Length: 39
Length: 171
Length: 187
Length: 48
Ligand SMILES: [Zn+2]
Image 1: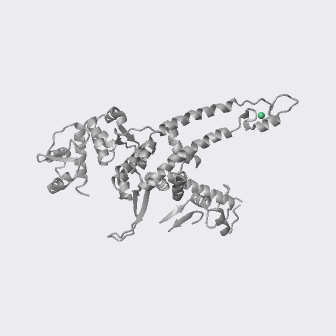
Image 2: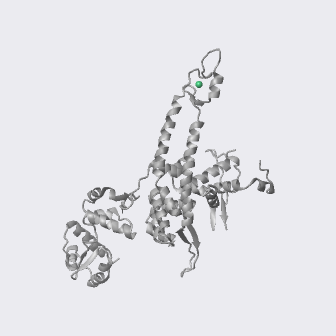
């Protein structure tokens, strides 16, 4: 909604740090599957 | 309107009596004579006696004659402390300092006598709320320790990452 | 609900957390399931301040929150909030504040060493031993920044480090007793 | 925001401050965001 993210399954605001940590947890191999060069 | 401000005036007269200090309860008709309520109808007085006098918490009934409850308001600092302890035990909460002030002369001296046992919290309306301290457990927190606490944020830490950190550190 | 878990929660919350929040944890202890409005009425605090504290509590997930919908007699839409404390979540979150406390202190000292010793007043900035010796000229015979043209003294760097070292020892003593309580919990 | 976090300021204060920080960063990257206010230069001229 504009420039903020909401995750609704109930519905909570999704701060940037949460996505940052999730992306950090993502592994390099999954980047190839997602079509993004990890290096 | 009719028959409301008169009741308010009676209740205010009771506060004025209590600033006077006459503990002895007074007759309602005599109160009316003092407050110039003779003109008012008798039926409204009877309705007040039956319903409003009992509903008012400050009012009390003794030997068929109505007056304030000398027990409700604080009279001594020791009783204030005991009431605070009981309120803490039963989860009542603190009491308003303005009400305690009108209740008790030199309430500020009473609080000074309390000292550490009594904890006062400011309010935007300047009213002071009082909470008993816990004698059983006493702890000290230092500002540097509170700061070292403050920086760290678990909200940054994701719950799975939590259980993962324990499992990683081998325990 | 063994008394050991309650004792751990009480001791940790009372010794190493805030008093205003401990006031709410007292209600959480008193009743397992409480309405959010009932928590407000028990707390006797302003909605905005309570909501700030509740946002902090939501971030730290000290107490789990659930949402329940039921139909009132009037029929108007009503939203009902339930907060209740979970021991399993609380234990990890608290342990987590505790653990990262130490990583902070280790990083602080890593930084103390990271800072460069040489510092020059005319320059007004830290200087690497590298830059200082390069600035040095063999013909002149004395090391000295080429730019500022004044001598460099490293004694000023030593002082704050010593001060921090003293603080760390005090922190260890203050945090020494809670570990025994944690052990009793793991028991 | 750093001072607010240092002082442990209100969670809603920090949330609104982070919202404004995000707005400023996104506006610096792009001032033509869809359905969002434009950042002027204190004179009515949108920033580039
Ligand atoms: Zn220099």
